[PDB]
Amino acid sequence: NEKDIEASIVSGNGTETGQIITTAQPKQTISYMAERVVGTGSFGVVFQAKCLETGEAVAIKKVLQDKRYKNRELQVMRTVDHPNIVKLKHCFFSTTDKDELYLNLVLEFVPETVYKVSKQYIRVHQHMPIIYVQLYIYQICRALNYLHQVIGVCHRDIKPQNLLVNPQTHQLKICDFGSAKMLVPGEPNISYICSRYYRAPELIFGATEYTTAIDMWSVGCVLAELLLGHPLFPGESGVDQLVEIIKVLGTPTREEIRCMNPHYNEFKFPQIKAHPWHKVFYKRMPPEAVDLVSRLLQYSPNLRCTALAACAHPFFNDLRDPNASLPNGQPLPPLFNFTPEELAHAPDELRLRLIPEH
């Protein structure tokens, strides 16, 4: 089936064009001038392109087709439609002499990432305004809710580089679903996923039956990173990453290790007392921020927050203000324009806090 298509290339240092069919009843020529790689990954590279027909700049993720492990990326991409997840526009094959097959995913062009924006603030040695922290983290959690509930998929690699940012609207969209999977109880999963800094400690203790909570740990770590202006848990390796977590949270209880991975059994380690959240962040930093960070960063995944619940956290009261705006006067992005399926997560309590009076 598939119904993915071939490309044709025009090359030679002067230009770099790829020609394509769009979709269909009569198919139509669509072309892209390639330019400027803006990221890689273990399988493929993301590069900018100009759609020669329309004019629209786009971001084409060239994925190297190596059997290795699951795709699922295209499967998810086709069937997702939400303001805070990236829109797939087209997909095609970009094969060349010998080598092998490349699958190209033509995504909408969003320039900056959270990683870039954070680097900007950090290199001026001055912290990033809370408004933005609230907007981005809120928009992650919203997207996560849709993924977890509507689509039923766990993104499974929430990291700053996988989060696009419009510098004008300050709209954020989740990127790169190479690691995403519909988590099924019973059928065991891969243990070793998610960038190490943002990796939930279930995955560290070799879990296999894990929930969507792993992504909510990741947003916990992103949020911390935005407040701290540096990675909260900068692990060098799996073991060093574990310790980095222990330095803040303290040593896990046997009950907590149960919740994380029952099969693991004992954990040979001394009992380090937790370095309290209060002394992890500034006195400046809003209590609501620390409260959220702490609820997101727990060992036991069940006690961890859910995406939609997080969205309704007091920390995002500011965003729900009727007079709320970007610091340059311009309005906030779409925040509360929920679809009914988005809010199929029952609680009316939640709904009421979630959508403001306006």
Image (tube, rainbow, N blue to C red):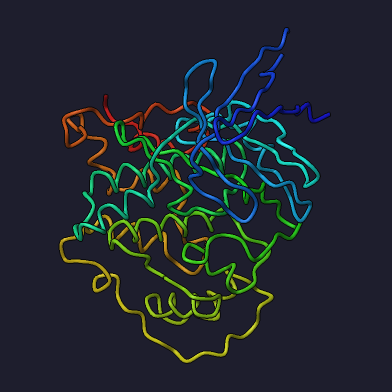
Q: Give the image quarter of residue 267.
A: bottom right
In the image, residue 169 lies at what x, y percent?
31, 31
In the image, residue 334 lies at what x, y percent?
36, 28
Q: Is residue 55 left or right of residue 181?
A: left
| Residue occupying the point 23% across, 52% down | 128
| Residue occupying the point 67% across, 51% down | 183
Q: Is residue 103 above or below residue 2?
A: below
Furthest residue toward right: 1
Q: Is residue 308 left or right of residue 128?
A: right
| Residue occupying the point 43% across, 28% down | 338
Q: How many marks?
A: 0
Is residue 17 or residue 345 the one in the foreground? 17
Q: Is residue 347 above or below residue 300?
A: above
| Residue occupying the point 48% across, 33% down | 343
Q: Give the image quarter of residue 207.
A: bottom right
Quarter occupied by the N terminus = top right
In the image, residue 152 lies at what x, y percent?
62, 41
Quarter occupied by the C terminus = top left
In the image, residue 17 lies at what x, y percent?
60, 28
Q: Is residue 191 above or below residue 15?
A: below
Q: Is residue 285 above or below residue 280?
A: above
Is residue 143 or residue 59 the one in the foreground? 59
Is residue 79 or residue 123 the one in the foreground? 123
